[PDB]
């Protein structure tokens, strides 16, 4: 290329979707291996614990729990099985109460630009798209999100 820059480029994946379930509920689907292997239908290994390891997509997506707040928010790493060495993304999820639904505010920063698109493309497809249908925490009709 024309521009010269050292290191690897990255991007941010800010996804804000709502769920037709209470925080405490979704608070498990993300902190419960089993629940994960349900919406992922693939060999997933989740360990609810500060520093634990969460694997999904048949061992294609792994990470590590950095912070865990009571039905409040969750901060962990996110990456693919084809990502560079020691290269993860800091993802900080948040569960909000809307009196029936839960607004999951995902904030990922550090996703490889080269895999940026791919990431987001195959991020919710399993994260939400999977649960929304699996557990039935999805809505219908067009919204002004």
Image (cartoon, grey):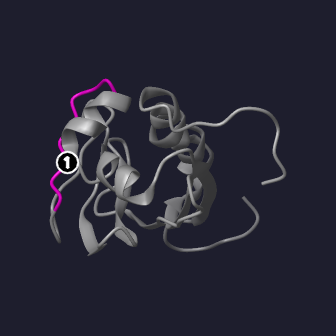
- Whole-percent x and y of residue 143? 81, 45
Q: Secondary structure at mark 1?
A: loop
- The N terminus lies in quadrant: bottom right
- Whole-percent x and y of residue 32? 22, 47
Question: Is 15 on the left or on the right of 136, as rendered?
Answer: right
109 or 5, nearer to the observer: 109
Q: Residue at x 28, y 26 (%)?
A: 42
In the picture of the structure, the residue carrying the numbered disc 1 is: 46
Residue 47: in magenta span: yes
Does residue 18 sit above or below 68 in this rendering? above
Q: Residue at x 20, y 36 (%)?
A: 34
72 or 8, nearer to the observer: 72
**Dividing the picture into quarters, in which one does residue 40 lie?**
top left
Q: Residue at x 46, y 42 (%)?
A: 127
**Dividing the picture into quarters, in which one does residue 61 lie?**
top left
Q: Residue at x 35, y 58 (%)?
A: 24
- Whole-percent x and y of residue 3? 73, 69
Residue reaching furthest front?
Answer: 99
- Whole-percent x and y of residue 37? 26, 32
Q: State the predominant SS element of the stretch in magenta.
A: loop
Does residue 28 sit above or below 33 in this rendering? below
**Dividing the picture into quarters, in which one does residue 41 lie?**
top left
- The C terminus lies in quadrant: bottom right
Residue 106: in magenta span: no
The magenta stretch is 40-48
């Amino acid at each position: 290329g024309s521009s010269g820059s050292s290191g690897i480029p990255t991007c941010k994946i800010t996804l804000k979707e709502t769920f037709l379930t209470s925080p405490e509920e979704l608070y498990r689907v993300f902190t419960t291996q089993e629940l994960v292997q349900a919406f992922t239908h693939a060999p997933a290994t989740l360990e609810a614990d500060r520093g634990g390891k969460f694997h999904m997509v048949d061992g294609n997506v792994s990470g590590e729990f950095t912070d865990l707040v009571p039905e409040k928010h969750i901060v962990m790493k996110w990456r693919f099985k084809s990502w560079p060495e020691g290269h993860f993304a800091t993802i900080t999820l948040t569960f909000i109460d809307k009196n029936g639904e839960t607004e999951l505010c995902m904030e990922g920063r550090g996703i490889p630009a080269p895999e940026e698109e791919r990431t987001r493309q195959g991020w919710q497809r399993y994260y939400f798209e999977g649960i929304k249908q699996t557990f039935g925490y999805g809505a219908s009709g067009p919204s002004s999100g």
